[PDB]
Amino acid sequence: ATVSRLRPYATTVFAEMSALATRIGAVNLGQGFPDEDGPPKMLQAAQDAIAGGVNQYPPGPGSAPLRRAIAAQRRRHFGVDYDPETEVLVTVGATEAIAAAVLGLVEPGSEVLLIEPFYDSYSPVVAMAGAHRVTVPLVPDGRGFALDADALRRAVTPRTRALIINSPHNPTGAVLSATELAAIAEIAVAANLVVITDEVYEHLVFDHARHLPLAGFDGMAERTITISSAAKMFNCTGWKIGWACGPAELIAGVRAAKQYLSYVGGAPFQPAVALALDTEDAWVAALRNSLRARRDRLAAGLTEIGFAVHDSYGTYFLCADPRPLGYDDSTEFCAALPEKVGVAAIPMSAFCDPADVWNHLVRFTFCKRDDTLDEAIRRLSVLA
Amino acid sequence: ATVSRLRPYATTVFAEMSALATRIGAVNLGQGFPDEDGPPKMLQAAQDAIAGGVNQYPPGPGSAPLRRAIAAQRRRHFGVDYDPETEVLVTVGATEAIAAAVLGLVEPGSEVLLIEPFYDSYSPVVAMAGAHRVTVPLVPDGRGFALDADALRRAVTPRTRALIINSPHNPTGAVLSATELAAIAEIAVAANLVVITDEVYEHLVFDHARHLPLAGFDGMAERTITISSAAKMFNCTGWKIGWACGPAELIAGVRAAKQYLSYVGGAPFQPAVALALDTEDAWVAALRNSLRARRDRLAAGLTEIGFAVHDSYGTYFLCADPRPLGYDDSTEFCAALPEKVGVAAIPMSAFCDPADVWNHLVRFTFCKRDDTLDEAIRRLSVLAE
Ligand SMILES: [Cl-]
Ligand SMILES: [Cl-]
Ligand code: NA
């Protein structure tokens, strides 16, 4: 039983799916997390931190070293230069930075624009704030997807306070082009919006796609809360070391909510993640490479089975269409999948506003070991 | 910088104090966390968990061993039986349990009763849910503090929907008596309240005080969310393994909000805390005896200096009054203390509704290393004139 505005979101298919798969013994290609660990020296650092007494509340905004390391990484990678003392806030994952940014910054009654299909937490967070979700779908292009900038512009109203942008994009694996980003900036500037970007896949762009933080576009620095995380970057989704970066005033509204949601967390992980950020670029590049190969590996397998596979330019997900196999209901496809076939995936319906080809798509995860991907493919092959 | 309703809460003094004292080398008796670590075997199990790959999202409601261990501990200590599958939710500390329980169960426009002085997160969490706090103060009872059940009853209106109780109590160190708990129960039932109880100091009761979980009282099991944490119980406030326990439908409401605030956290700590709950009762008992001895030392030292020290029956906090020393402004006293005296503490004004004893009290922490605690007392001794 839950408050009225959270009722639509009281359960997710994500948990019903991972629990089902877990003791069907179904290969889980629905999971939002990796099989493999982060950098060995990062794991060791976290172990040494516990052993060395780093087990109490860290400073409210995050340890100084971790805040410096985040600013140093954003500067190193992208040339955006944040002040670690006032413009960087460590959070309990990107998940908390998202929740706190909306609760801290968006007044009840305001509209928040979402790009559809959207990550699972955006709508309920907007609803928790008492704000109104307005969704603008991506459009196919032809094997991938693209922003429809005119559609986004039309969606803005005087009630729009904020826009949440997620690139590289979960679930489609789209990577917003500079042109798309420039169009988003023009709109955000013209309407005087706050923009919250969700960049947790910043390290995962494939095939000459390039991650270009929106905060770097004209007019954007002063109005963007940029969110990312160690979760996927360093394969430590269970550590929940994320961060929001932006203008001190906006970071203060984020901190204003955040400090009462968790206060702080992840004490021994903060020095370990700071170390990873400072030192593990080469490991991250090898991760990205390993995932590009696994993407190709899964795509090739789905394709040989007879799925119509869409391009993925980043993240560790790709979307595929089972219509060529004879499966026209993808929510029912995925529902039946573990018991019929012994694989789990997520239907695209999970990421879409309840009232285009979207309803047919399935999201598959490829951050699994080689062998597991292969086994998934073998199991799925019975559909042919 | 911030939405209207959180503006009063945008900054805490718990921030400006921590940092003032940290880097002028003032002994910090304002802190809300211990100097020392939890059970060695719990620390090692967390390190082992990291080394063993336990680094990814745990299950949405907490790992099964942890939920089982919470239910086993609540049974073992209180004889209360929760179903670990449906009636136990692991959260990101008690703090997130509180936030998610209010956001998940309390409708905008509701009144939420709070007992003043109150923990820092209650008021802003109520505001974030679009609800209205109604505050009822404790009253002096000799050297200690008491619930005024009549004031509490009178504070209920047709729009009251929830009540947050914290016992053992931060900041006074009061521990609600069965008589007080039973009076809360009557009120909650009569007004059909959801009650959230913050029991993070469940292990820290002293002398003849007893911790009696409110969920145990008449008509309460069906309307109560009981919250606690490994934070203080096992000296790991940075690990944020908290939990909420209660009827399946209320817990689902907590989970509904919680799963979008953090989703989950603390992966390698969950097996470690499960272990500590299952096996480290002896260590927790010694910790409690150890903190009783540090309380008595602090109280004796403040008293000898010339503070009027109040009774404390639990938590690792005690309250004292510096008026007999000649300090009639305790917010100012605390502001100047780190520079003047080399010690930091929190004034009671930081726990009161910004709308008489309270304004003069100062909360001191005694979960300090013994010698650190002695140094603080030593430092405070300059105030004897
Ligand atoms: Cl371009
Ligand atoms: Cl009694
Ligand atoms: Na506008």
Image (tube, coloured by chain):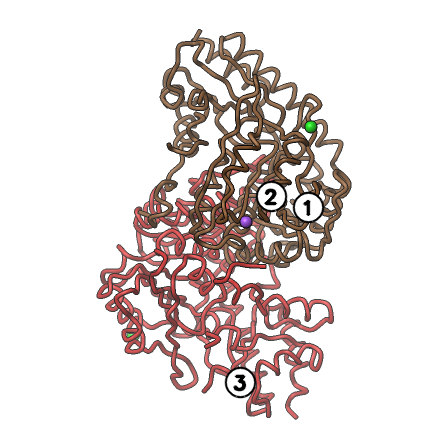
Chain colours: A brown, B red
Task: State how far apart marks 3 and 2 are (Cα).
Answer: 54 Å
Percent across and percent down for residue B226 are: 37, 57
Say which of A150 and B25 sits in front: A150
Mark 1, Cα crowd under 10 Å, few <14 / some 14-19 / many 20+, is some
Relative to B131, B159 lies left or right? left
Q: Are discs 2 and 1 less than 8 Å apart at CB?
A: yes
The answer to whether the residues at label 3 and label 1 have Cβ atoms under 8 Å apart is no
Q: Residue at x 50, y 50 (%)?
A: B92
Q: Quadrant of the C terminus of chain B?
A: bottom right
Mark 2 chain: A
Q: Nearer the viewer, mark 3 or mark 1?
A: 1
B231 with respect to B209 (left or right)? right
Viewer-nearest of labels 3 and 2?
A: 2
| Label 2: which secondary element | helix
Q: Mark 3 — on which chain does it sit?
A: B
- Residue A49 coordinates in the image, percent (x, y): 67, 49
Residue B292 place in picture, x, y as percent: 50, 72
| Residue for badge 2 | A188
* Amino acid, disc 1: Gly
Numbered tag placed on residue B113 in the rendering: none
- Chain for numbered disc 1: A
Real-space Cα separation, disc 2 to disc 1, in angstroms: 9 Å
Between discs 2 and 1, the one toward the N terminus: 2
Tell me the quarter of the image containing the N terminus of chain B.
bottom right
Label 3 and label 1 in one chain: no
Same chain for mark 3 and mark 2? The answer is: no
Disc 3: which residue: B321
- State the residue position of label 1: A219
A315 up-or-down from B297: above or below: above
